[PDB]
Image (cartoon, rainbow over all chains, first blue to last red; front, side):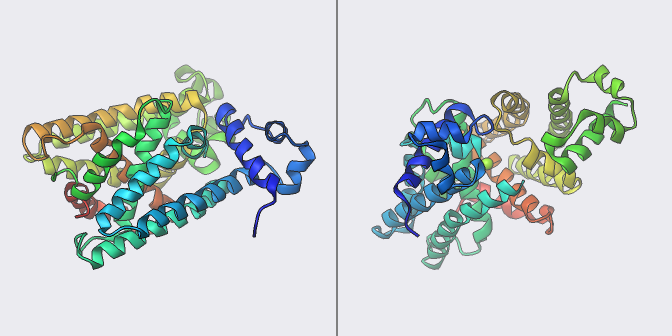
Amino acid sequence: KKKGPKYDQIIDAAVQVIAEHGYHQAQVSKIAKAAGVADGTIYLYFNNKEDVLISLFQEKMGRFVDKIRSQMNEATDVEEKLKILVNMHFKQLAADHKLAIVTQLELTELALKINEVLKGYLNLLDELLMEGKEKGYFFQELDTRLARQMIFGTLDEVVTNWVMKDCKYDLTALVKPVHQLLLGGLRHR
Amino acid sequence: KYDQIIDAAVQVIAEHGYHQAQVSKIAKAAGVADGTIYLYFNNKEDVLISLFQEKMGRFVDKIRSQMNEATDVEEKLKILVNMHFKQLAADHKLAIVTQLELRQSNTELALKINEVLKGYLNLLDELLMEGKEKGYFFQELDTRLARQMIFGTLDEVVTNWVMKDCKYDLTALVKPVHQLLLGGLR
Ligand SMILES: [Mg+2]
């Protein structure tokens, strides 16, 4: 279903208030003022703060994935697809520091829901891994589930450390060695 | 009664969550007066930190002693993966604490937890430097990135197991996790 115009507006403002103040100390009224709307307008779109948070994540992630998926199918080799995934992951977060703060630090039943949204990205990883196995790029005895956990767990840990250091350094400088490290492990490159 | 308070803290935090976990709840579960809790800890945060610090310290110490007995750097890595999974597989409530409850939004609590975690990350750093110097790992290996890969991967595997109600055997994953980290995807 297509969004109301203010929908996108509240979410954007939600990112800013949550990052700047923290999730617990964020309030619907402060999100309203930041989005430039009346408090009651927010409740037309969302029921409460946690509904804003999950809609935020669902929305941001849905586009995050489709953009990665797009950059991927206009490519040849599957290791360049992996490179594309790794660079699209870092770039999108590098392009939005406040969003990175929300997804890495400010993100119970809540956790379960966040995990469900994440499944879309994990599915994309699975597709990539299945393809690479099938075409003999990745070794064939590779467990797709474990490989997905290694890839996601590594990218997420790199990003989270960057957010902990106040997004100070160039995250996209890590694209190539992360990519290489995923492909060759500790032993090879 | 220090160890009893620690064990009780795990139980309570795992059952109720760090937020609704009250110190008087911990005292009861440990079988001591509320007052005795404050001979060791001065608040609920200090209980959580000292809990992590006590578990982690023990964990890291036992890994170090088992490694210093190993003959092989890849064996040392396997020992670390094995101990990481074995300790949590033996104590699901401790897993709930390390995987879910130690995960803070709060800046300053998260900061002090991370400080404790650094004892483990430093151990991974040492092992990685050793492996490079002895030629197990390639000489241009980025130590910090490799540390984040190993830790990020282990933590993700444990979290997915915790999220699936610990229903499969986490220790069965030691060997394939070990092989994957050493050889990568290709
Ligand atoms: Mg992680």
